[PDB]
Amino acid sequence: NTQANVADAKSRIVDVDFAKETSAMTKYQVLQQTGSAMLAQANQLPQVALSLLG
Amino acid sequence: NTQANVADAKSRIVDVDFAKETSAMTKYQVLQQTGSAMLAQANQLPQVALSLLG
Picture 1 (cartoon, rainbow over the protein chains, first blue to last red):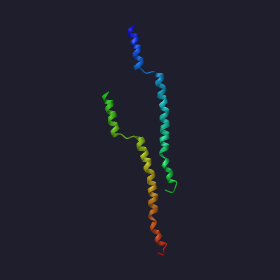
Picture 2 (cartoon, rainbow over the protein chains, first blue to last red):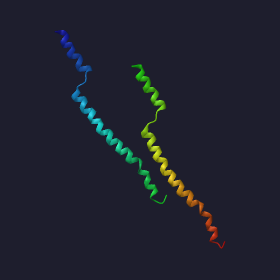
Picture 3 (cartoon, each protein chain N blue to C red):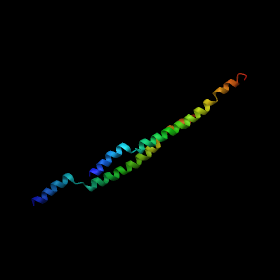
Picture 4 (cartoon, rainbow over the protein chains, first blue to last red):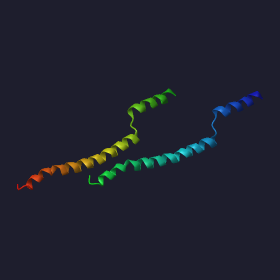
């Protein structure tokens, strides 16, 4: 009996909850694609200087 | 385990960060076109001497 209850206590501390973890993993995937598009588009900001005659 | 951690340490030293590198590459492309227009236009500065009667 006591072995089962200690296993309960030990899992709440070191084990992951997939419901919590899966949401976070999908959460950051969107942020990565958002970050890549923003960075690529922000890199060509200085090309405005070429419009004003070199 | 130790192999993975050494791979971490080795990549921070010799490997490029594309975020850093891509910005620099686009950074210099603009400067090249700016430099070419300035140099071409600076080359025809001495043509003012032809206005004052040869």
